Amino acid sequence: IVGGYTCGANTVPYQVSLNSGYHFCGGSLINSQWVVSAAHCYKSGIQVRLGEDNINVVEGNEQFISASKSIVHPSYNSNTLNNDIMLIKLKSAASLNSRVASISLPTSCASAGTQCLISGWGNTKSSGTSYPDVLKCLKAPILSDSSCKSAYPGQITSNMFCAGYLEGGKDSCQGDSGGPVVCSGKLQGIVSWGSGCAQKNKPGVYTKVCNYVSWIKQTIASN
Ligand SMILES: CC(C)COc1cccc(-c2nc3cc(C(N)=[NH2+])c(F)cc3[nH]2)c1[O-]
Ligand SMILES: [Ca+2]
């Protein structure tokens, strides 16, 4: 997260760290046995870390659970990153409470101007790699489709939305991938891609979760 602030331990109880011997992507806890992340964060050998704050120190509240299966959306396209969403089932359920809690899926899509909270342990520099030890937060507004399309002409599908600051300086970045964009308490986006990080006129692009609610529900139900 570039230009964001330290969230405060456990103030984002649905945030998860996907770890394969190092933190590589974020994710969101949606029920005690399932996490939603981005399909491009897929890989085998994933350990899901819940209740984390500083990822290099065990300080208490952490639950490390291995993934039972990862289900990448069947129409995920790695070239365009359309349908960039993945569900991960955990080998055992997590114990939910106040430091570990699931976030709700939306009932409607959000509008441009809605303010949302983006969080993650991703890069904090737009030029160079500086990965933090504790969770960073950023409040960003959803942009209108016209500003999103003027910024990425020909690359925005109806399953994506832009959120951020066109002046640059504040944005999600590599490492934040797969994590949550929560607005009014509902999971509305998944960190997916962008051109560089915090560059002027190049906002972040997020998977539009409201378009996958029926799929998430049917897939969890049948697995
Ligand atoms: C291990 C894999 C997850 C590799 O994934 C990646 C490798 C390099 C960069 C990214 C990445 N840059 C990103 C930049 C932005 C942005 N400007 N708001 C974003 F929203 C997601 C990004 N994801 C990324 O997701
Ligand atoms: Ca820790």
Image: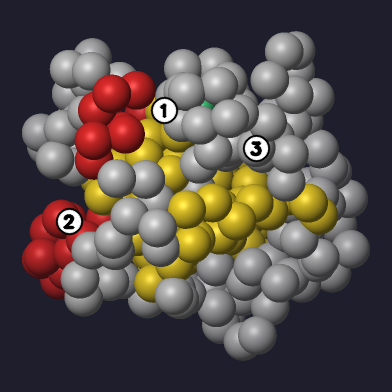
Q: Amino acid at mark 2?
A: Tyr
State the residue in front, 162 or 26.
162
Tell me the SS state at disc 3. loop
Q: Is residue 141 above or below residue 73?
A: below
Measure the C-alpha gap from mark 2 to mark 1: 18 Å
**Left or right, residue 103 beside residue 131:** left
Residue at left offset 17%, top offset 56%: 212
Q: Is residue 89 above or below residue 148?
A: below
Residue 152: x and y in percent read 30, 20
Q: Is residue 6 above or below residue 29?
A: above
Residue at left offset 43%, top offset 44%: 163
Measure the C-alpha gap from mark 3 to mark 1: 15 Å
The label number, if any, that marks residue 193 in the structure image: 1
Residue 22 in view here: no
Residue at left offset 58%, top offset 20%: 199
Tell me the SS state at disc 1. strand
Q: Which residue is mark 2?
A: 212
Q: Residues within 10 Å of mark 2 (few under 14, many from 20)?
A: some
The label number, if any, that marks residue 170 in the structure image: 3
Foreground label between 3 and 1:
3
Q: Ligand 1 within 8 A of label 1's CB?
A: yes
